[PDB]
Length: 272
Image (cartoon, rainbow, N blue to C red; front, side, top):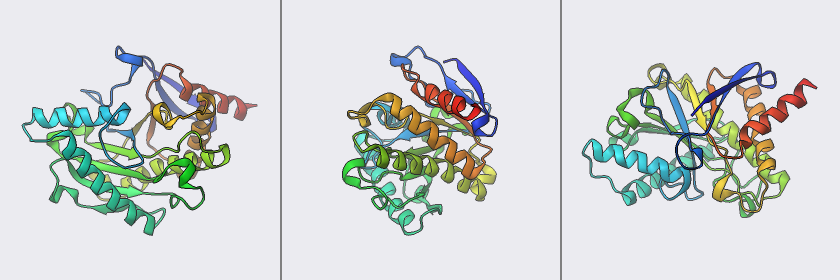
């Protein structure tokens, strides 16, 4: 996948990477590289039920974790990972909702074979400023996990951080959709910002985040991809402005290049 790099003055003159098509179906970008130069945390396009598994990118995350587990000789099945990830992330979201804008935490490594430590963060309490009936439930919920070495992709120490986030369903009205999308992006960037400030951030910082086009695929419903590119672009602008982060942004590939086009439009709008 060609890492196309473009500078954005609307994002404080930051370089953003937009991976081109890979050899895989629909040019799907790999979750993690076998030989990374920096610590990239990839953001799982999560489900409203908060499990790791199933289909789409979420399924690829599960397959990757399970394959590495089997490789390192651990009895980990799809149902184990689905249920455990679900349990941990349900509990953490409850804690996160008690204290919006704060990074909450539990030592999952004490009882898990997959997760060493687990975090959560919400910019806005779900179902308060929008209705979960149109967006889906647990929208904006953002989780960050330090993976155990025995499930770390490609067995590389630098690939042992992942994120998991829940995007708004596309059939939500524009007003609610855009608002939820921004809240979600704030959750991602806020979680990283807050996490890098902790002692864990001294040892295992997130130096870049690899993002899909959130809300795409199965979460689209009837919504047009253009409206999603714009929602993402504007959400990214607000998040960068809020946290002014050092973290590098990378966007995974999908055939319509909507993530790129949305931000190109934001750049054009900013520069004129």
